[PDB]
Image: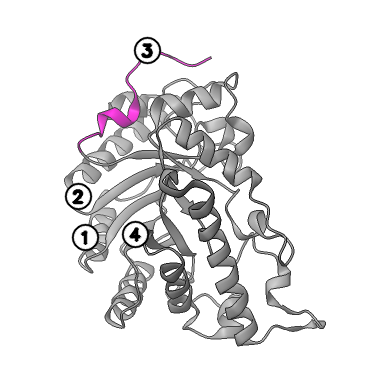
Amino acid sequence: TIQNDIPDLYSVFKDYFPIGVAVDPSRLNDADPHAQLTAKHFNMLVAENAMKPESLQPTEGNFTFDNADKIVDYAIAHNMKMRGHTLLWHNQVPDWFFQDPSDPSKPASRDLLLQRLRTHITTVLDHFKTKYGSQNPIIGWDVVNEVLDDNGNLRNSKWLQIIGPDYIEKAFEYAHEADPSMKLFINDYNIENNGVKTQAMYDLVKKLKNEGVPINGIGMQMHISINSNIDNIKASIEKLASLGVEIQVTELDMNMNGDVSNDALLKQARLYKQLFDLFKAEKQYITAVVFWGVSDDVSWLSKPNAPLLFDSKLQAKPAYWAIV
């Protein structure tokens, strides 16, 4: 059971930005305490998996929107905004995209993979626009996800191998043409460390925006750790925001490196307090902060961990009280 009378987390930030959470379609029923936490503390939702490529078009032409629509319906019923995650990725993407269908031992051509990307993006955006119309809660999409490698070069996924570097520009062109009302983001991790990957994200977005690509924002996943440096995160946010794009914190959690002791929980609370004070200090750039999971027992990180504001018993942690 949850604590029903403590402060609603998102209301603490009502004069700053929405506070969201990533959810599983099976944890939205009234009797599920995870759903109760979701409705109480968040005013924005993201599908942790149900809107990834494999979760929407597992085989060619066979679209599977039921789980994504269950999350959308819940968001509408709870007056929540949503982010769409994600139109393109090199993981959780079916192999059929990249195969020649008449000889699956060979790769699809650049034109066939671009047409498949255009059809997937257009069908996905047209599905939510035609089914929900003005009630569509999705305000924007992660058009591409994790397109940089660790060294800052473009990740050599099958998209890059088959199409070349302009696949990124093409994904944003297709999404903007399908629904011009959507805010379009490029999303990535490790771009908060003010290292070579931050610089490569800045250079890539500067280049594409100068070329007229409709990129409206950068999503900083923010899978941080108990040892992260606030100064590096601040410098990264400011550098990326200097491009004249929105910043969203999209998959926030804190990796404890195996130390879930009470002392580490206190250290986590001080760091999360500093992180949210930084986000408030950057409110002219940040337009959403989303946590990657509702509570520690449903975090994607392997065990042991304690990455979020609500523990494995769904109770508010020291970090929750530090922030509120």
Say the numbered circle drawn on residue 238: 1
**Residue 59 found in image quarter:** bottom right
279 relative to 57, above or below:
above
- Residue 307 belongs to the span the image colors magenta: no
Say the numbered circle drawn on residue 193: 4
The residue at the point 68 percent across, 52 percent down is 64
Horizontal and vertical percent position of residue 140:
40, 55
Q: Determine whether, in the image, residue 7 is placed left or right of residue 164.
A: left
For the residues labelled 4 and 2, say whether their Cβ atoms are less than 8 Å apart.
no
Q: Secondary structure at mark 2?
A: loop
For the record, the magenta segment spans 1-15
Amino acid type for the residue under numbered disc 1: Glu
Q: Secondary structure at mark 1?
A: helix
Amino acid type for the residue under numbered disc 4: Asn
- The residue at which mark 2 appears reads as 282
Mark 3 closeness class: few <14, some 14–19, many ≥20 residues within 10 Å: few
Quarter holding the C terminus is: top left
Mark 4 closeness class: few <14, some 14–19, many ≥20 residues within 10 Å: many
For the residues labelled 1 and 2, say whether their Cβ atoms are less than 8 Å apart.
yes
**Residue 262 found in image quarter:** top left
Say the numbered circle drawn on residue 134: none
- The residue at which mark 3 appears reads as 5
Amino acid type for the residue under numbered disc 3: Asp
Q: Secondary structure at mark 3?
A: loop
